[PDB]
Image: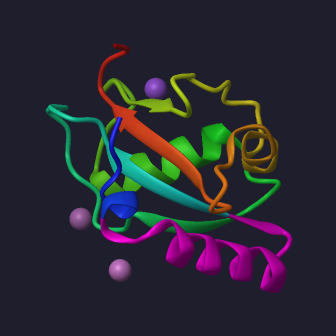
Amino acid sequence: MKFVYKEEHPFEKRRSEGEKIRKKYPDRVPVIVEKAPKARIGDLDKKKYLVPSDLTVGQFYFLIRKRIHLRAEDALFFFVNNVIPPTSATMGQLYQEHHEEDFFLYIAYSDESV
Ligand code: NA
Ligand code: NI
Ligand code: NI
C-alpha cells in the first residue's frame, strides 16, 4: 500500500524522528495510523501516536474506535504488513516484529478484511 506519511517525508527525515523518539522514550513505540484506500469509514484526525509498549492491540482498537466514533458492532480491522494482529498482542510485540527501517510501526485500518 501507500502511506501519506511516507509520501510526504523522505526516509532520512522519518528515520531521524523515529530513531530520536526511540531513544528519548524507549518504553514507547511510535506508530503511524492511516485508513485503507476506499474504506467507507471515518478518517483519523491524528495519524501519529506514541503508545506504551505494554498497551494491547485490543486497547488500541478502542482508542481508535473512540477517536473516529465507531461502535463495537462496526467492523474495524488493523493491518500491519498485511496481517491482522490478535487483540492480546502488545504494541511492543507488534513493533518488535513489524517496525520499518525508519523506526516507525505502520498500521492501516479498514472496515473489511481484503
Ligand atoms: Na474489530
Ligand atoms: Ni511533515
Ligand atoms: Ni469527534
Residue at left offset 72%, top offset 82%? 20
Residue 69, percent across and down?
Answer: 28, 50
Q: Which residues are magenta?
A: 8-29
Judging depth in this view, the residue of 70 and 1 nearest the camera is 1
Residue 84, percent across and down?
Answer: 56, 23
Residue 83, percent across and down?
Answer: 57, 22
State whether the magenta stretch is mostly helix, strand or loop.
helix
**Quadrant in the picture for residue 98:** top right
In the rendered image, which quarter contains the C terminus? Answer: top left
Residue at left offset 14%, top offset 32%? 40
Split into quadrants, the picture shows ligand 2 in the one at bottom left
Relative to residue 2, is residue 101 drawn left or right? right
As displayed, is residue 51 above or below residue 21? above
Judging depth in this view, the residue of 27 and 99 nearest the camera is 99
Judging depth in this view, the residue of 79 and 59 nearest the camera is 79
Residue at left offset 55%, top offset 34%? 80
Relative to residue 52, is residue 2 drawn left or right? left
As displayed, is residue 46 above or below residue 62? below
Relative to residue 10, is residue 59 drawn left or right? right
Judging depth in this view, the residue of 13 and 69 nearest the camera is 13
User: Residue 21 magenta-drawn?
Assistant: yes
As displayed, is residue 86 above or below residue 52? above
In the rendered image, which quarter contains the N terminus? Answer: top left
Give the farthest residue toward the top: 114
Residue 85, percent across and down?
Answer: 63, 26
Number of on-image labels: 0
**Rendered image coloring scheme:** rainbow
